[PDB]
Image (tube, coloured by chain):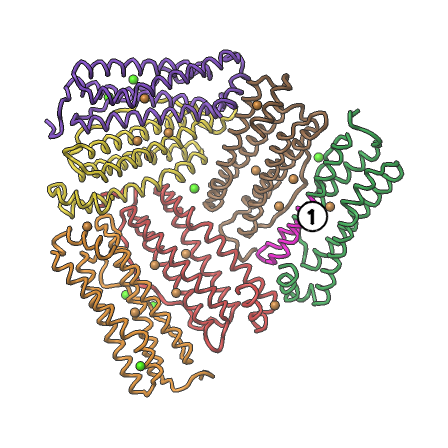
Chain colours: A purple, B brown, C green, D yellow, E red, F orange
Amino acid sequence: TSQVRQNYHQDSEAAINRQINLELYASYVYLSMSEYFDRDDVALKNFAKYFHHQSHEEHEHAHKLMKLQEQRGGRIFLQDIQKADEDDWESGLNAMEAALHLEKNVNQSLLELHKLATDKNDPHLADFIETHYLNEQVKAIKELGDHVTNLRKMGAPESGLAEYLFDKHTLG
Amino acid sequence: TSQVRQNYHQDSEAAINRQINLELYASYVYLSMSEYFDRDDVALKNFAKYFHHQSHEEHEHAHKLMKLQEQRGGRIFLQDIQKADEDDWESGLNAMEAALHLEKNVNQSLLELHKLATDKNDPHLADFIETHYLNEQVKAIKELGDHVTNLRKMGAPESGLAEYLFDKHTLG
Amino acid sequence: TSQVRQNYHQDSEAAINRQINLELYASYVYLSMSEYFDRDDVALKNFAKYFHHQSHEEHEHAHKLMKLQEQRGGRIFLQDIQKADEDDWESGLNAMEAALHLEKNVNQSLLELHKLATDKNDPHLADFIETHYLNEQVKAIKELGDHVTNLRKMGAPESGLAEYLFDKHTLG
Amino acid sequence: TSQVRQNYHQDSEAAINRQINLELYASYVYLSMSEYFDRDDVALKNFAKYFHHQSHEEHEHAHKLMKLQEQRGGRIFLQDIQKADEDDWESGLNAMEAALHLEKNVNQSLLELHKLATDKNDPHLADFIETHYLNEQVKAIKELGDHVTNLRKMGAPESGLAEYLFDKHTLG
Amino acid sequence: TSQVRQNYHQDSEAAINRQINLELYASYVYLSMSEYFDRDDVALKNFAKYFHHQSHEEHEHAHKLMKLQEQRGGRIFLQDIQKADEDDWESGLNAMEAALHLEKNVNQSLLELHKLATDKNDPHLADFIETHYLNEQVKAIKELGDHVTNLRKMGAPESGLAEYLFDKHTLG
Amino acid sequence: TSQVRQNYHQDSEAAINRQINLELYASYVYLSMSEYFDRDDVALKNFAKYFHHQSHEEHEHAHKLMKLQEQRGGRIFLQDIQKADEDDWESGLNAMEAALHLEKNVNQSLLELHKLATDKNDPHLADFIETHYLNEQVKAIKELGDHVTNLRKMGAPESGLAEYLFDKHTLG
Ligand SMILES: [Ca+2]
Ligand SMILES: [Ca+2]
Ligand SMILES: [Ca+2]
Ligand SMILES: [Ca+2]
Ligand SMILES: [Ca+2]
Ligand SMILES: [Ca+2]
Ligand SMILES: [Ca+2]
Ligand SMILES: [Ca+2]
Ligand SMILES: [Cu+2]
Ligand SMILES: [Cu+2]
Ligand SMILES: [Cu+2]
Ligand SMILES: [Cu+2]
Ligand SMILES: [Cu+2]
Ligand SMILES: [Cu+2]
Ligand SMILES: [Cu+2]
Ligand SMILES: [Cu+2]
Ligand SMILES: [Cu+2]
Ligand SMILES: [Cu+2]
Ligand SMILES: [Cu+2]
Ligand SMILES: [Cu+2]
Ligand SMILES: [Cu+2]
Ligand SMILES: [Cu+2]
Ligand SMILES: [Cu+2]
């Protein structure tokens, strides 16, 4: 056992390891989306930039969790980063919809992680999740909802003009 | 024979002369396209600027080849610069499509030039083509593909609004 | 007929198209001369620079004419740009002499163009030629005459020292 | 088939997809190593920083390959990013030794990729690998060899003082 | 065998060692030429400066090759640096002619080195030679050809005035 | 005989030519040492930098002697630059010891050169050696002695840690 370990339950350590992998997965989904919009038959450069930014943000989320694990005296156990469900994201609107779904899934996992911290009387972990994760998720979900809404109201995905103009005026 | 000539095959010298003319031709096609978009009944100023830029880029491509010829001790033999297949380029989308076709044709000629350099064991010429031409073509082809894609998805060439908005937001 | 076309005779439109091609031809002659002086067995770098500058100047002359055509509602009809009469320009003095001859030929064509504008009662075209072309030609012809004179008096083309020193002290 | 695709063999497209995954794997190995050195019972912060830098470098290597795929008109097919062979890297010297082995493995794959490009007469791909990958690998391998050598000569991994001083004076 | 050595043939290692010596030899020839022009009975200071610069350039060429040897895990085996064929270089024109001959000889050796790299399927070495050596040689050969040409046309070596003026206007 | 030659004995001219070669030899020994420390199985970068600096310093020493020869009206006769006694310098301490021996040998030759100048009543040469060479040698010998001493006292060459720390704290 670590010289630093204090009030850190085995279940919490395990849950943190699972959360690290999920953040790395989210980052990979975003990378997949990013590259999709750089295809010659898609060619929406600001969508590509947006999802590239989101990919690196999720990477930072993974970093903080790995830091938390080391600080608390837990042991990081990395797992395979699974590829995304799709190779072809269909459209700007579909990718945004898929991103929204992903972020709500990550949020659900974080809420379960928080409940575990509360149940194990780990207020440091509870606050770590609150401070660095919970509001970030809520903000991310709201932004993606905003994007989905505009794209829909503009006539996406049927209107390619809608996705082009959104790429230019919101994302660029 | 030149005091500088070394490992420079007669066939390579001839192929370089042919490539010079093709680069000058490409430059002329782009000039034709440029001026078309400045017509009072077309009036797409950023299309005009874009193709003007492409015209001068091809001119630089011709310059480097002429320099290569002199450096290697070959003799430049210039040929007539043929006018383009069209006077009237129809639309923004059509010009982009025609440009894409042109760039792929120039690329094919460069690949054949590279094979000749390899076959004649001329690694200087091989690398000259690799370094200054091959990736430039690949980048140019991809960009034109991107442009064609956006214009199509926006509703060009039927939608004049599409070509107007593309001129403003991508090319301007 | 153009929505902009006013007082613009079919003969003038045709003559402008012919003048565009001649300016492009002059530019090409200068390019040929430029590259000649970059040959390892010629090696007069400031001659090369001088004629390169002249090449791009003629290009600008072609640009203004193409602009005039579009502004007046004429239609640009481009033609093949013919290669120069020579591949080998012999010497600094010979190239200058050939350039002088070329500029006087271009000037003759411009004077005929001006007479046509006067005959067709087209004062806009008449002034366009006067303002942008006629004095430019007179200046160019005089400069080339000056250069020919100095080279001759210095002992060119027999004296290679003369051409070397002229390259350094006048053109450099 | 892509509007941009030219001279791009199905085997090359597949090999590029495999190389993308390998670069992502290398990045993940480095991340694993990075976090290991941040453990309270390891605590070599400059080792951690060094491998973190290497992780992001491999990420850039993956980015350029993904860009190449899109530019050439290939389709990116992402795969699971496999976790590293180890959770516990034992020591500074062992991690450096493992990194050296990894880089030589990546290099072998790049050399095979280059042979395939040569065999398929794809000089653009050949030069892309040469320009952006081959010398980068050679430099990386040499640096890791240098590091392994110093650590060994200093008395690692038996001497914890050696690894501490190396962390401070070479990596910091 | 080196911990870093990969895909590096014994013949390539040997050829690199031979090339290192040749670059050091070229540097020494240039040094000899440099000092010759500083003789009180020669006194062409800009010739001296020019060849001094060339001497140090060849030294850098030797440095990069030595670096390549270490990076690839080869062992540097230095050899005697042979003195030049002449003590007395006769004239500005003769030295330039001798330099031209030297550079073409070095170039021939580099081309043979490149063929060996290709034959041994060593694309890293092939590109190293292409990137850092082949175009540098072509540029150097062309420049020396240019210099020889001007000196000849000016009346060298019979005309001491020609060599004096060339020293002042081209080299100074 | 030179128009500038005055009070310059044939023996002095010969001795200066021999000294030039010895300075070039010393420079080459240092270059050999420099590259040795850049080996992947040695990897002492500041040793490499130190000896590289010493190599170029000896080159300057050779330059001043060549200048002296020309100024006095002597004729430079260059000789082959002999490779060093070793390819493998064993260690930091051994190289420093070998450098110390080399510098004392060069110093002995300079002292003999000075005696010859005194014997031939050549006070210009005597002072040239005094001013530019004698104290430089004494300083160089003392510095190398200092380095040898520290390395020995630190536990070199048996202690690789000693050579590593010396590389970092004295040479870096
Ligand atoms: Ca899977
Ligand atoms: Ca025709
Ligand atoms: Ca013709
Ligand atoms: Ca697995
Ligand atoms: Ca290459
Ligand atoms: Ca000899
Ligand atoms: Ca020997
Ligand atoms: Ca004194
Ligand atoms: Cu990224
Ligand atoms: Cu996240
Ligand atoms: Cu233009
Ligand atoms: Cu081009
Ligand atoms: Cu807008
Ligand atoms: Cu130009
Ligand atoms: Cu003109
Ligand atoms: Cu990171
Ligand atoms: Cu990589
Ligand atoms: Cu210290
Ligand atoms: Cu020097
Ligand atoms: Cu060289
Ligand atoms: Cu002068
Ligand atoms: Cu050096
Ligand atoms: Cu010395």
Q: Is residue C46 magenta?
A: yes
The rendered magenta stretch, by its main secondary structure, is classed as helix
Question: Is residue D2 in view?
Answer: no
Percent x, y of residue F143: 22, 65
Q: Nearer the viewer, residue F81 or C72?
A: C72
Q: Nearer the viewer, residue D18 or C124?
A: C124
Amino acid marked by disc 1: Val
Percent x, y of residue C167: 63, 61
**Residue designated by label 1:** C29
At numbered mark 1, what does the secondary structure look like: helix, strand or loop?
helix
Q: Does A148 sit above or below residue F163? A: above
Q: Does B97 sit above or below residue E132? A: above
Question: Viewed as shown, does residue F40 lie left or right of B127?
Answer: left
Q: Nearer the viewer, residue D25 or D172?
A: D172
Could you say which quadrant of the image residue A64 lies in?
top left
Question: Is residue C47 in view?
Answer: yes
Percent x, y of residue D115: 37, 35
Percent x, y of residue F131: 32, 76
Q: Residues within 10 Å of mark 1 (few under 14, many from 20)?
A: many
Could you say which quadrant of the image residue D10 lies in?
top left
Q: Is residue A122 magenta?
A: no
Residue range corresponding to the magenta coloring: C32-59
Q: Residue at coordinates 58% horizontally, 66% vertically from top-left? A: E152
